[PDB]
Image 1 (cartoon, chains in turn purple, yellow):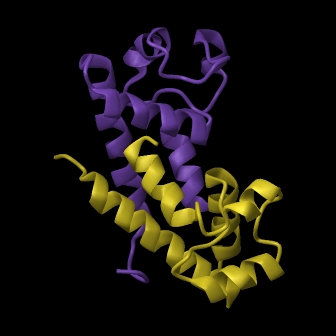
Image 2 (cartoon, helix red, strand yellow):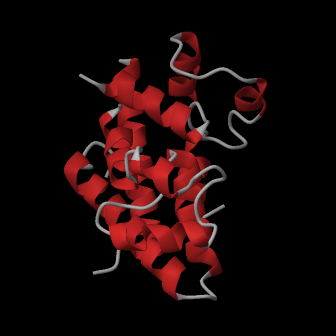
Length: 92
Length: 86
């Protein structure tokens, strides 16, 4: 209900939703929707991968799930998607 | 343990709507501006009066693109698009 949505919980749920989509996008060759979801998160939030899934990030990059210009080294110097999700809900 | 796409999209729209209300009347202005800039939108078709205030109070980013699609691609649509992968 509008007026009762908790910030910590919604941020947790969005991070979980993202992690679910990323895991499926990597493992499921027919997961056209999951791949589209993570591509949209990555482009919208300017991120690639998450801190809970660091061992996946190179597979994520290889399979063109991150925006142009994203690469292994450059991504190490960027915040991960979970931090970007926190920033969104915190207004930073 | 799965987060349902429709439920989380609904929750995020409600989170935005509350921030919009609070901003027009805390950190609500920063939250609204962040949503607007990140999602490339500036209000909601369901909250037209609040949308007017956003435009009068510089809480919306620049672009003919934003304005041409003010309600055609509003923040609720952008939130839907985020969770649906469009």
